[PDB]
Image 1 (tube, rainbow over the protein chains, first blue to last red):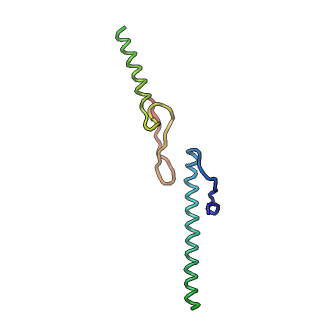
Image 2: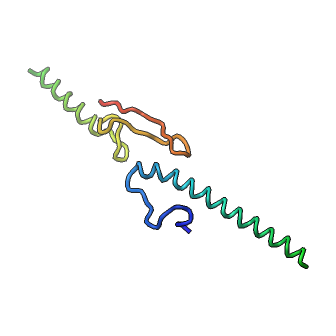
Length: 55
Length: 54
């Protein structure tokens, strides 16, 4: 959710300089989102491996 | 007097032609702004083009 990425529900730019900073903000958001999702996928594969072992 | 009047008409024509030189509300010749900065990379760094008045 936006709050977890560091974006705020009110977030926007009203002038060109704010947009020039928003580029870097959205870069950081995309980075952290991909890292979180990669951790979720790793944990899912770990659940699958444990499921086969339990069987 | 005739030559001077033609010179004045050409002067006004230069003012008009300089005022009309705009592309989608932005100009690099009219002198409205010191500079313009077009994008140069995905990080937002900008290629710079210093304005030239006419």
